[PDB]
Length: 329
Length: 26
Image 1 (tube, each protein chain N blue to C red):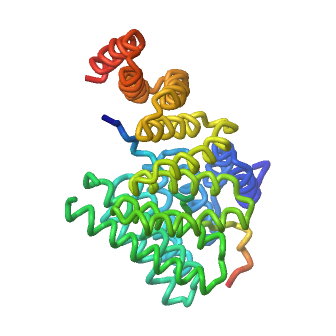
Image 2: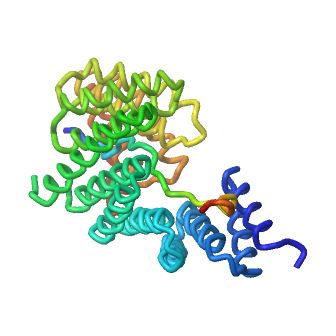
Image 3: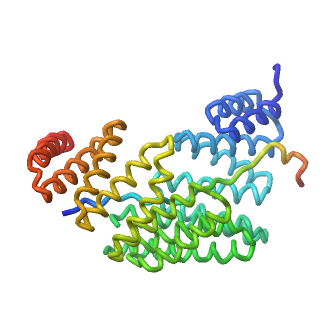
């Protein structure tokens, strides 16, 4: 062996931290191959490999490695390690759609954190439980009681998280709680409360110079103001989102903000502006081969052109809408 | 008249992390 288990694992850690989980996995898998009798080290390798696979969207392997970690953490009596493995299992189960199992795992992380008087772990588990319940609520077709109950549970967990990270003075974590809390209120139809939460999210984003969080807050504020009937205000927030979005490598962000602006201007009965924004979304949806998006663009454009009496363009987009609609039949 | 999109911007998610650099922990 030219490198030891520990040496290989350390390189994997660094590669993953650097954003190259693919390369990191190779080093962790090399480390597991070499092996070690140090069970704490082995559990750390499994945990890191589980997270790397999670980030590479191999959720089955993520689950396998987080389970291997859980097994070892229990056998050596590493309570913190068991809590972490359980939280990781929960978050993996969440993405797989196994929400009720995710709840148990994430609650286990919470329970052990409390047993250990680990408030940082406790807070993180509360955030995770809010996230599981939020996604659970959406899985039931977001007004059905199963949706309302899960989303309300999400509010409760996010509020408990926010209290604890306020006690811990973790301002960036407060910002994250506010964002997810706001979007949960939004789904529940509590639009004023969504505005209150996203306003805090935005203030916190600005305190940190966090341009991504700022952009998210603008987008979510726009969304909430649409449902409050405040279309002009929504347009102002969506324009602020778009100013940032148009600079991003991920073109979907600009596309969505343009679609939203298109709809806002339709609601304001400014059909010329609506068309401008909808044409931008159409171009990007085509670039990204998003046929559902392209179809929705053609519908929105046809509606707007019709309102202006531009039947030549409206009918161009009717044809394309019909074509795409059959394709996505 | 309108087809509203289902997009909203959720916050970053976490995982719990371990490191072999915790070798000397009790």
